View (tube, chains in turn cyan, purple):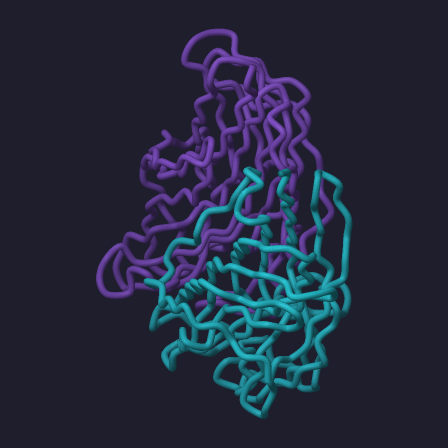
Length: 236
Length: 236
């Protein structure tokens, strides 16, 4: 009779290696990601498993594994994709030194799939992008080969668990490794950077019936028209 | 007795004039701001009034006026300041051409004040920043004089209406006009740009007792420790 309502919010990050704006970047294995878990107005931190869904020498797709308690759920997710790169060395430790851009393939974007013991139905995955002006230059590099500064997602789906240890995964747009997407400031030596993946907010509303209201965020402006799909992503 | 819970969310924008990154910018009068109003899972668009709270030769502080229904309210606001610039014309209207940077003055950040027929108590206006790296270059200019890309706020207060048609206002960090903060792409002529002010999310919780789900805004990557401002802003 009383329906559960669970929220996860987090800003996943990962470590990269970058030399010059003319060089491809390398990627560390993804770390576990600190998310805030909220249910019944008790609040705690949790680490969500994350890894590369796929990786090759051109790109890697990030994935985050989200546990689902047994039940039937309406799942609502917002994702604000932006990859600023930042130094790890003083006195410039937390200062943004550039970004890694996305491509403009909205079919390779924010979506969900089955990780364990869930069925995902009635999906609607929306994806948008933000381009750069043809004269804009960041660290000596232009944005005229499809490079996008931001890739946003808005997703709603229906998730039914089929046992214990149930989870779905969220994939993001690909982390591009080729040099045309690398706008991290150039150094003469390979230099580690921290790279944000984006802001992710997840709500699990049991049978869409908890009635729970919360504060919200607006959709970013300047973004393209959305490409939408009902398809989900298959586990590789 | 039903305790109301009201949310406003929007990304205010305003029009500027900019020529080359070596020139200062000019600020037009602020327009009305499109916000979403959310109460009892019922959503509508509304235009909030905005204007420059103050302006001197170097900078201007924006203000946005927020209606408050009769009663007593606990107020929670999150603000994510980022000022990307873009053309007002075709093509490129949706393409980011650059940004206007902030200074690192955390004594001048997001805050609230009385607009009409409210008393504001228990104000705590927290402010953070994110620097650009001195070596980063955007549109021919470096971040080597303390320029900040982002200025975020987290505010709580208590608002009690003391008359009809009550409202408070939100101020933001200073919009800097000097050339060293101008990273909008260079044009040969003075050219109008749209400039975002930032993401604002306001929650009004009647007597703090609606039972809304309390989340917390994820602290964006690389932001400074918060500096608190206690006094509210006074109208001239």
